[PDB]
Length: 272
Ligand SMILES: O=c1ccn([C@@H]2O[C@H](COP(=O)(O)OP(=O)(O)O[C@H]3O[C@H](CO)[C@H](O)[C@@H](O)[C@H]3O)[C@@H](O)[C@H]2O)c(=O)[nH]1
Ligand SMILES: [Mg+2]
Image (cartoon, rainbow, N blue to C red; front, side):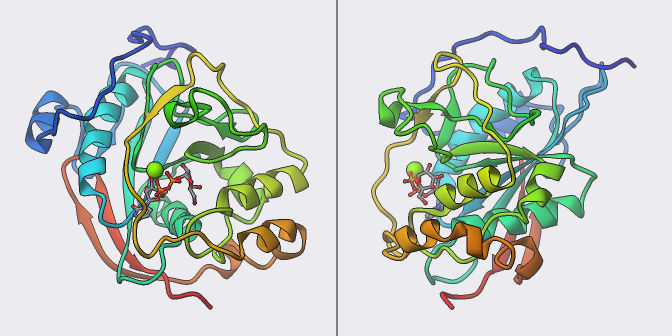
């Protein structure tokens, strides 16, 4: 086997993405036979240098997940990546903590395979063009740059939410993501600040290839806007050394391998 081509030849470009067609995971699996237990896939006809762990923060979003799986697996295989899907499920009914869930995902995934790239994706975001590769780059990568919920515009140049990817070393170099952001908002801005403070820039696909669709939904109870988010992101400089991968604590309650993804239910504590 030889190293895969820089740009995969199975790419079709823009795709039709819609969510009023409720799916069947059984069909998904039948339609994606190369997907090994736990949502794992390795190209059989070339060597991909991208060992990608896709981490999805999760809590009561099965319907979104189904659509996510229906759409990304065929896409990811055409992108010729050697990947695994990790749904990090917050146990309990306390305040949601997206970023801490993403950290847990980084550590747990590494216990399965030697991934060197991490794609952090909201459960409700689907790329509209398979040319927007779900891999890592020389600089941190903002993948969902043109979301339809933002009329295909970046809400602001430093926006880093939705879907992003960090090589294993870029992630480590910033001490991971913060574990101290409970509730909705700001966590993505803190992460951006970290990348900046570490002297890194953000890489992005053009607005066309980066178009992506957001599954319309209402606010979830227990993930209400975090009023402390403004003060927190204003002090990332002072807190990233101690709040991160080095101070991460959690309790894996269960690991389930579904045919299309691995579900890790974890207890990540409460607002300290
Ligand atoms: O009860 C919940 C709350 C959140 N999530 C997960 O966390 C993600 C973000 O939560 P929401 O989609 O409600 O939030 P938004 O659509 O506003 O998400 C946007 O703003 C967020 C504020 O924290 C994140 O920064 C972000 O990635 C961005 O896409 C979801 O995609 C999902 O993966 C759940 O599974 N269950
Ligand atoms: Mg959303």
